[PDB]
View 1 (cartoon, rainbow, N blue to C red):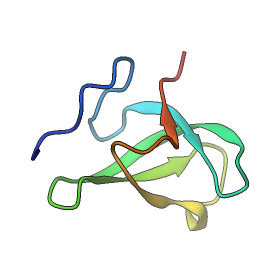
View 2: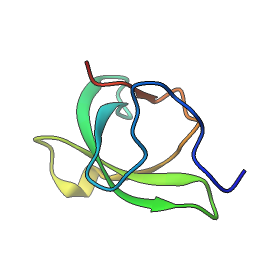
View 3: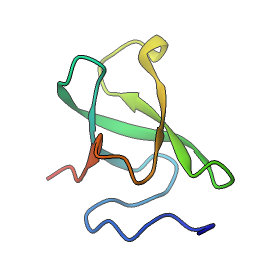
View 4: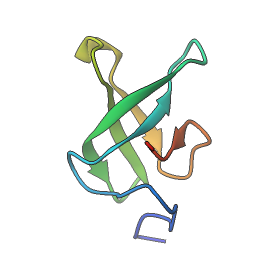
Length: 68
């Protein structure tokens, strides 16, 4: 589908916050920088990390969860 999935506690908007799993399998509070509706992926920034670690993650990924 052309719309993000219903993932309760995740808001699919630019600047919304969630928790994201990095490439070393650690969870960090993160921010949505961009949303690609064609590829169904979002550019995720890991808070208090360099933007060099920013990653395109599929919006249905198990690497995304709600920030409580």
